[PDB]
Length: 256
Ligand SMILES: NS(=O)(=O)c1ccc(N2CCN(CC[C@@H]3OCCc4ccccc43)CC2)cc1
Ligand SMILES: [Zn+2]
Image (tube, protein in one colour):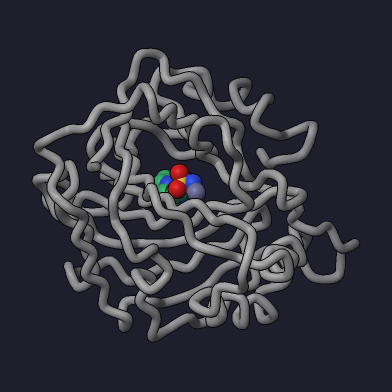
């Protein structure tokens, strides 16, 4: 599976029939069709920078993984009774600045999207068990609008030179990803899925109303990462964004 013509999001249903399910992500948030929900608490993030572990080139993208053995790094509040434990963050981006986000707002595409992924450690023992469960994952999505260089991205961008090719990894320590989140934590939420295979309908999405910035040059650094293993012909990671999927009667709630 991948993002190419031959293995891309249009082909995914062949290997993963859930691709055409009823709770697929991402979606276009229509602001006129959302519903202010009264019982949504604010989002509380409390991350410990010592839980940052490793940055990895996975060939379609790159992941920053966290230690998830205890509750040092948690997401609380919003639509949740339970505490969710941080395990990874990553980005999606497009061929050019014109597209790149997975979620769209009133049909407007942003240049990139930040995902912060968490698992339900109140109800399940591991990521392995939580990952396939209706209530198992919580991902925060932040839309990234092309403009001014984002200095909080610097430590991430500075690490990419050590994981240029597929399978390469390095230590990535002493990092609190709440520093990447926008000042306002006003959000939308809907029940949904992983935006790539295995596409489990296990995700409660938290989509920030406020965007963060990224430069054209910072997006060039993402696209300068390589999908091939060391010594093969260089294949740039041009894009890794899935097109928006039908709501199929689901309701997007707003905190605001
Ligand atoms: N773009 S996104 O934010 O929707 C997003 C997409 C994919 C992920 N991945 C990590 C979590 N997923 C859990 C399933 C995983 O792979 C299958 C085997 C297996 C075994 C044991 C434990 C876990 C797993 C895998 C992909 C996370 C977030
Ligand atoms: Zn993602």
